Image (cartoon, coloured by chain):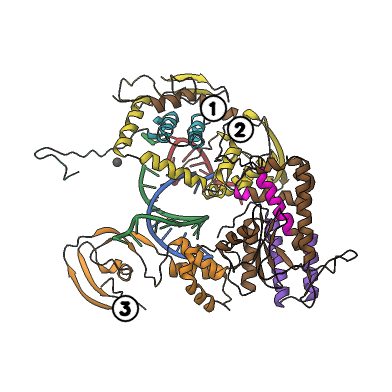
Chain colours: A orange, B purple, C cyan, D yellow, E brown, F green, G blue, H red
RNA sequence: AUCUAUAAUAGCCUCUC
RNA sequence: GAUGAGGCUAUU
RNA sequence: AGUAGUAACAAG
C-alpha cells in the first residue's frame, strides 16, 4: 500500500555522495528491543509458559490485551503468529549507503531512490512522523 | 523459545499434563470419566 | 591517515598478505596472549581461557 | 630449529619454535619471541586503557550465561566415539551420552562451564566407555556389499581417548 | 549433621530441597542450615496441602483413615514450592490465566481453589507479627500470607482457610522437631551464621595440568613459571 | 543522537603452494 | 568426504 | 577412450 500510494518526481543525473549509516529497514508502528518483543510475544501467544513477569513488559500490558483480543480464535500455527508479531515489533537496522533520506519509509525504496550518479524523487504513501519532519 | 530446566523432560511433561487435566476438569472441558482416566494414566507414569 | 600526513612528506600504502599465516602462528604464543590479556581476572577464568591453546599445542 | 621432545601425555613428537633462534633469511619462520609479543601486548594495553580488562569481564559474563546447546551451532564436527564426522548436534549428544556412561553428568547442569569441567575430568578417566557404530556386511547379488550400521558399546584406554580428543579431522576444500 | 535431616525428613523432601538449592546455586554442604530450612518449609507446605479435598460439589472436606484412593481425586491445595522454577512458574501462570487473576510478581508457595488465592507460607524465628508485616511489604494483599514461628506464634492472613486442628498439628510437629534437634545438640549448628563468598569453580585435573605444563615455550619449566613471568616481568625494549 | 538489544536453520561473498 | 570466523540474505 | 588435473570418475 505504501508503494502504491506513492508519487514519483523527476530523475536527475549528477554526482551523489552517499554515506554509510545504520538505518532502519522497514517502518514499525511500535518498536521495542528483541528481548522486550520476545517477552510481549510470549505473553500474547504462550502466557502459560511465559515465566517471570518481567517489569519491562508493564508498559506494553495494554497492547498485549489488544493482541490477545485479535488472536483469541485464530487457528493459525502459533510460531507463524509469533514471527508475524516479531515482524511487526522487532526492528531490523543495517548499515546502508544513504543520501539525504534515512527514514524507514525511504529505506524500503532505497534501491530506486538514488545511485552513485543519479537521484530519483520519491514520495512514499501513508503518514510521516512529526519528529522526522 | 528455547525451554529451560535442569529436570527431565518426562517430569515437566507429566506436570504440564496434570495441570492441563485439572484445569480442564475445573473449567468443565473434561467430564468425570475422562478426568479419572487421565489421573490414572498420570499416576501410572 | 591522509589528513595526518606530515606537511611536505610522503605517505605510502603497502597492500600485503602474510605467507604461511596458519603454519607459522604458534598455539604457545596464543597461550601467552591469553595469559597476558586475562591479567586481572579470577583464576578459574584464566585457566578456562588457557585450556584451548593448551589443547591446540598438543593437537593431532 | 626449535626444541624437539616427546610428549609425556601422548608420546607424540613435539616441536616448540617459540623463543627459538631468530631467522637468518627471509624464509617463513615460526620462531616468535615471547618478550616481543608481550611488549606488543603492553603497547596495545597502554594505547587502550582498560580494554583487556573489559574484554575479559565481558567474556567471563558471556561464558557464565552460556549453555551447552551453543555447541550445536557448528557444521560437521569430528566425533571421537565413531572417529568420523557427524553434525555438531549429533556429536554433542553422542558425547553427552558417553559421558553419562562414564559418570560425567556436568551437562545436566545446563551451563557450558560444567560441561567443560566434565571434558577436563574425562581427560583423566583411566578408561572410557561409549557407544559406537559398527557395520554388518551382507552379500547382495547383482556381488554388491550392503552395510547395516548399528549401535554397540565400546571401550578405549586413557591414552587413546586423550589422542582422540586432541585429534583434528582433515578434508579437502 | 545431615543424618538427622535424612532420618526425619522423607526422601522426597530432601530431594526437592536439594533441587531447589541447585536451582539457586548453593552448595548443600557449605550451607546445611538452608537445607534444613527448605526441608521444614516444604514439610509444612505438604502438611497443610494434605488436609482438605474438594468434593463433587466443590466444597472442602477433611481426610481420615479407611478412605480409598479413588475418593481422593483433586487436592484442596496445590503445592507450588518444592518444584523446579520453570514448572512452578508454569503452574502459577496457568492458575492465574484460568482463574481471572493477575499473576503475582513473585512465586507463591500454595494455591487454594476454594478461595482461589495464592498463599505464601513463611517460617520466622523472631516475632511473628514483624515477619508478617515484612512479607506484607512486598505485595500485601495480592497474596494472603500466613507466618508460623518456632515459639508457637502464628500470624494467619485475613481470610482464614484452615481449621484449628491443622494449625495445632503443624505447631505440634514443629515443636517435636525443635525438641528432637535440641536433645540432639543441633540448634547451635543451625543458628551459626557462616556464609562465606562462593563463586564459580573450574579446577584442572592431572592430565590437563600436565598438558599445559608441556605447552610452554622454551625456557619455562612449567606453566606456573610462565604465568609468573607474564604477570611480573616488564618486556619494555 | 540506534548507542542498546538480538532464538534457530539454510544459502551467497571474503579470508597454505 | 565437504571446516572455523565475519557480513548480508530468506524462512520458521 | 574421454573428462580432468598433483586424484579421481569412467556405477555400486
Ligand atoms: Mg591483501
* Chain part drawn in magenta: E22-45
Q: Which residue sits at x=39%, y=73%?
A: A29
Q: Please, which residue is most extreme toward the left here?
A: C8
In percent of width and height, residue C45 lies at 49, 37
> Which residue is disc 1 drawn over?
E211
* Viewer-proximal residue among D20 and F15: D20
In the rendered image, the vertical position of residue E199 relative to residue G7, given as above or below: above
User: x and y percent of residue A79 in the render?
Assistant: 55, 67
Quadrant holding the N terminus of chain D: top left
CB contact under 8 Å: marks 2 and 1 = yes
Q: CA distance from mark 2 to mark 1?
A: 10 Å
Mark 3 = which residue? Answer: A125
Name the element at disc 3: loop
Which residue is at 29% across, 59% downward? A21
Residues at circles 1 and 3 in contact by the CB criterion of under 8 Å: no
Q: What distance separates the C-alpha of mark 1 from that of mark 3?
A: 67 Å
Is any atom of residue E50 visible in this view?
no
Which chain contains the residue that carries disc 3?
A
Extreme right residue here? E66
Front residue of this view, candidates D83 and E161: E161
Residue of label 2: D123
Amino acid at each position: 500500500m505504501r508503494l502504491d500510494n506513492a508519487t514519483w518526481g523527476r530523475i536527475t543525473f549528477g554526482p551523489v555522495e552517499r554515506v554509510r549509516k545504520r538505518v532502519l529497514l522497514n517502518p514499525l508502528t511500535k518498536e521495542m528491543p528483541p528481548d522486550e518483543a520476545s517477552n510481549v510475544i510470549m505473553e500474547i501467544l504462550f502466557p502459560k509458559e511465559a515465566g517471570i513477569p518481567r517489569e519491562s513488559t508493564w508498559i506494553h500490558r495494554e497492547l498485549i490485551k489488544e493482541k490477545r483480543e485479535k488472536l483469541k480464535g485464530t487457528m493459525i500455527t502459533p510460531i507463524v503468529l509469533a514471527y508475524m508479531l516479531e515482524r511487526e515489533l522487532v526492528a531490523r537496522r543495517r548499515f546502508l549507503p544513504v543520501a539525504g533520506a534515512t527514514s524507514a519509509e525511504f529505506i524500503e525504496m532505497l534501491h530506486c531512490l538514488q545511485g552513485e550518479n543519479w537521484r530519483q524523487i520519491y514520495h512514499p504513501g501513508g503518514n510521516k512522523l512529526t519528529e522526522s519532519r | 523459545r528455547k525451554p529451560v530446566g535442569q529436570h527431565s523432560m518426562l517430569e515437566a511433561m507429566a506436570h504440564r499434563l496434570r495441570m492441563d487435566a485439572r484445569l480442564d476438569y475445573e473449567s468443565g472441558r473434561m467430564s468425570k470419566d475422562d478426568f479419572e482416566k487421565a489421573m490414572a494414566h498420570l499416576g501410572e507414569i | 591517515m591522509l589528513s595526518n600526513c606530515p606537511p611536505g612528506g610522503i605517505s605510502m600504502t603497502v597492500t600485503g598478505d602474510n605467507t604461511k599465516w596458519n603454519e607459522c602462528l604458534n598455539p604457545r604464543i596464543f597461550l601467552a596472549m591469553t595469559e597476558r590479556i586475562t591479567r586481572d581476572s579470577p583464576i578459574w577464568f584464566r585457566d578456562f581461557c588457557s585450556i584451548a591453546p593448551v589443547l591446540f599445542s598438543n593437537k593431532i | 630449529k626449535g626444541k624437539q621432545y616427546i610428549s609425556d601425555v601422548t608420546g607424540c613428537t613435539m616441536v616448540d619454535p617459540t623463543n627459538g633462534p631468530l631467522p637468518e633469511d627471509n624464509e617463513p619462520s615460526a620462531y616468535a619471541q615471547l618478550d616481543c609479543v608481550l611488549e606488543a601486548l603492553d603497547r596495545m594495553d597502554e594505547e587502550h586503557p582498560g580494554l583487556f580488562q573489559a574484554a575479559s569481564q565481558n567474556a567471563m559474563e558471556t561464558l557464565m550465561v552460556t549453555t551447552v546447546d551453543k555447541l550445536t551451532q557448528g557444521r560437521q564436527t569430528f566425533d571421537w566415539t565413531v572417529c568420523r564426522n557427524q553434525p555438531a548436534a549429533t556429536a554433542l549428544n553422542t558425547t553427552i551420552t558417553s559421558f553419562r556412561l562414564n559418570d560425567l553428568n556436568g551437562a545436566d547442569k545446563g551451563g557450558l562451564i560444567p560441561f567443560c569441567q566434565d571434558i577436563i575430568d574425562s581427560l583423566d578417566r583411566p578408561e572410557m566407555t561409549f557407544f559406537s557404530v559398527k557395520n554388518i556386511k551382507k552379500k547382495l547379488p547383482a556381488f554388491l556389499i550392503k552395510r547395516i550400521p548399528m549401535k554397540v558399546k565400546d571401550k578405549i584406554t586413557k591414552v587413546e581417548y586423550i589422542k582422540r580428543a586432541l585429534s583434528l579431522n582433515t578434508m579437502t576444500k | 549433621m545431615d543424618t538427622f535431616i535424612t532420618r526425619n525428613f522423607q526422601t522426597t523432601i530432601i530431594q526437592k530441597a536439594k533441587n531447589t538449592m541447585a536451582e539457586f546455586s548453593e552448595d548443600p554442604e557449605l550451607q546445611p542450615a538452608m537445607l534444613f530450612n527448605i526441608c521444614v518449609h516444604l514439610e509444612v507446605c505438604y502438611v497443610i496441602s494434605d488436609m482438605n479435598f474438594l468434593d463433587e460439589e466443590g466444597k472442602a472436606y477433611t481426610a481420615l483413615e479407611g478412605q480409598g484412593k479413588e475418593q481422593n481425586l483433586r487436592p484442596q491445595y496445590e503445592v507450588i514450592e518444592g518444584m523446579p522454577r520453570t514448572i512452578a512458574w508454569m503452574v502459577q501462570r496457568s492458575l492465574a490465566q484460568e482463574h481471572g487473576i493477575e499473576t503475582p510478581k513473585y512465586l507463591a508457595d500454595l494455591f487454594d481453589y476454594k478461595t482461589k488465592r495464592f498463599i505464601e507460607v513463611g517460617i520466622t524465628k523472631g516475632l511473628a507479627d514483624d515477619y508478617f508485616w515484612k512479607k506484607k511489604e512486598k505485595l500485601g494483599n495480592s497474596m494472603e500470607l500466613m507466618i508460623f514461628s518456632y515459639n508457637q506464634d502464628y500470624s494467619l492472613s485475613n481470610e482464614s482457610s484452615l481449621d484449628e486442628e491443622g494449625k495445632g498439628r503443624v505447631l505440634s510437629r514443629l515443636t517435636e522437631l525443635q525438641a528432637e534437634l535440641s536433645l540432639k545438640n543441633l540448634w547451635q549448628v543451625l543458628i551459626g551464621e557462616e556464609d562465606v563468598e562462593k563463586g564459580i569453580d573450574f579446577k584442572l585435573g592431572q592430565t590437563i595440568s600436565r598438558l599445559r605444563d608441556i605447552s610452554v615455550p622454551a625456557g619455562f619449566s612449567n606453566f606456573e613459571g610462565m604465568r609468573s613471568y607474564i604477570d611480573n616481568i616488564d618486556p619494555k625494549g
